[PDB]
RNA sequence: AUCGCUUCUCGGCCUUUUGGCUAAGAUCAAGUGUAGUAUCUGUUCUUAUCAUUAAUAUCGUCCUCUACCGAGGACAAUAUUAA
């Protein structure tokens, strides 16, 4: 319950932006962003893994439907 | 009384049906064996079909485009809560 799906990411968003946006909720152990090597850009989503499930939970509550780089993002348990 | 439907009864067609001939064309009794096949009689096991819900989000195959890779679409159940 530590891994979150994060969608609706603008092109300018990268692993650094994600780390900065989610670290306020707790320490993070991993951030994965699937890439399209033909374009070299991400596909609009990523997975953020928190150290603690309780922190992942607080992040879902405060970040789902929040704004990042001008647009609304979607956040929920990945699985 | 008339029209339509249904049940029952009955008449008509029913050669639609017996498609040649001769010396009725001729003739006229029975088990011997086996194995093999078929039928019947019992000996044995018949009563029923089996297995939570609500809400939210999203590896394999097929098609298309671009240069094995990437993107998009569709299909195949998954997760959480509560008795």
Image (cartoon, coloured by chain):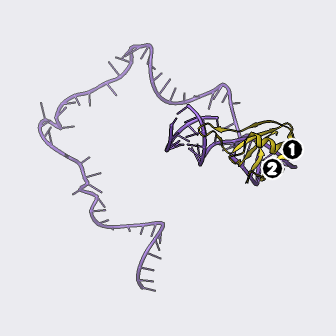
Chain colours: A yellow, B purple
Label total for image? 2
Quadrant where the image shows the N terminus of chain A: top right
Give the residue displayed 79% in from the left and 51% down from the top.
A64
Residue at the image point whose x is 66% and y is 38% from the top? A35
Regarding mark 2 in the picture, which secondary structure is present there? helix
Q: Earlier in the sequence, mark 2 or mark 1?
A: 1
Q: Is residue B17 left or right of residue B54?
A: left
Determine whether the residue tagged by mark 1 lies in a helix, strand or loop: helix
Position above or below: B65 against B59 = below
Measured along the vertical axis of the image, is residue A63 above or below residue B5? Answer: above
Residue A22, picture quadrant: top right
Asked if badge 2 and badge 1 are on a common chain, one would say yes
Tell me, yes or no, whether the two marked residues, 2 and 1, touch with CB atoms within 8 Å.
Answer: yes
Q: Which chain is home to disc 2?
A: A
Can you identify the residue that label 2 sits on? A63
* In this rendering, position of residue A63 left or right of residue B19: right
Quarter in which the C terminus of chain A is drawn: top right
Rendered image: mark on residue A25: 1
Q: Nearer the viewer, residue A58 or B36?
A: A58
Query: Residue B57, percent across and down?
Result: 72, 49
Q: For residue A10, say whether it is visible.
A: yes
């Amino acid at each position: 319950k530590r891994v979150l799906y994060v969608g609706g990411l603008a092109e300018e968003v990268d692993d650094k932006v994600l780390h900065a946006a989610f670290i306020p909720f707790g320490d993070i152990t991993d951030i994965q962003i699937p890439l399209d090597y033909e374009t070299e850009k991400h596909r609009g989503f990523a997975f953020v893994e928190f150290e603690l499930a309780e922190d992942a939970a607080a992040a879902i509550d405060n970040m789902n439907e929040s704004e990042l780089f001008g647009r609304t993002i979607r956040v929920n348990l990945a699985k």
